Image (cartoon, rainbow, N blue to C red; front, side):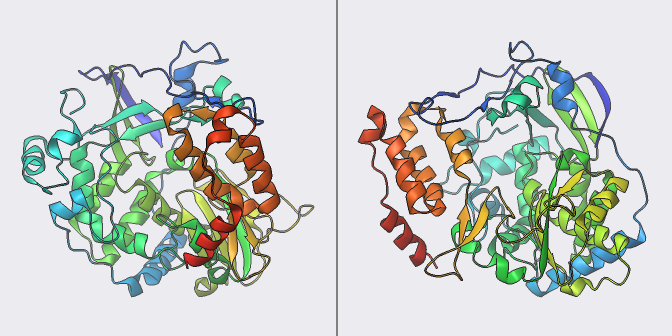
Length: 455
């Protein structure tokens, strides 16, 4: 991705509020070093220029025609999707706004992107009546292909990323474009949400508690895994063209216009309008699905390029955006694939760091930050294991201390998969300060019983 122009826009995106994150009652109880992201250039923790840091994720584009390996990768991925019979038909506007099977109702808490005019999603949306008349009028009034509004994401970051100014950005699409994309691709989204696995190659919308046990069965060969640096922003237009070819082969036609809208995008930040060629915007309706579909093309492309004689029908993969876990019957060198990725302008790191390191296996591999651990009693059931370090970092901060009981409970639903001893220790530390001693916490046996019973 590359910013190809920058100028005064004509509008003024308000400066962000200060962070909603503050030390929680548990800040001193637990170890941790993350802090809220830098949100403005006057933050005293900065050790470098803020604006340069946040836009540094755009590393340029590898301009090129689609190559022979991409054409084969696209064809194989389309073959994997065809048994799902994705309908190219639009879904009704009512479904796009208020939900259907496989597609949740439109998120009412994210920006309408409208934001300069005091019109809120709440005004246009009425889930009780499921009314589409105000949205229809707004689509008529403003159309689609509108700019994205840039917000800095209010969230915890490592201390290094705080002082390097490596905060993340939300590139929020207009409510018009979200709605229009959901109309055009709603059945595709639903198909993906309803079929996490190795046909979609997707984990978006999955429930790790139940989906984890399926993963080793679907990926039953010699596994490998990747993490990327700046995946979204590093994507070159050629990868969006591959995605367009997949959609065309599914039977879409004029709907590739929605991919052009993601490939060549207009962004609003402060008083600037900047235009980005390549780079997936973060806050579009299909951001996650399309990032995932593109990763399915990428990994195949790299495999075919590096190895002659690959039979892709034995390759299997599952991705969530940039995060990839994959399988092939014979061992490969994922470091060679990573170098191949460089040729296409991608920066990826294999889980296997070299010949001296232990081979990627079910004991050391991660997906969605979680490890995999077979249950003692039922070793065919796989626990998703969020590291306690992650839970420790998150429990030390709160955006609203009135949600402490809800936040802590949801952390317990993650923590207990680390085993009974780790969970008792976690609960004991929670109950080392007043508020914690008063909280309701699920018992280990109760969590395990609910877990076993969600299959």
